[PDB]
Length: 88
Image (cartoon, rainbow, N blue to C red):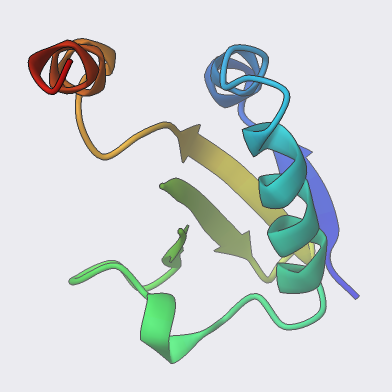
């Protein structure tokens, strides 16, 4: 029941996550559109910001729009890469 919208920086971020991710995220996002305000996912101190497991979105009631603002990863890309190397 909520419209989707992406911040342009986040859409650019989205186009670099890879094939596998931006699909499982697309799934969880469209699910969020039904009822965006999930208490278990609300960022601390932030009245309108929520997380998807990361992805962050802003709920804009005045427009009924879910605004995806930030999407990325827990660590730097180098940390996962170095972790893969470290175990070889």
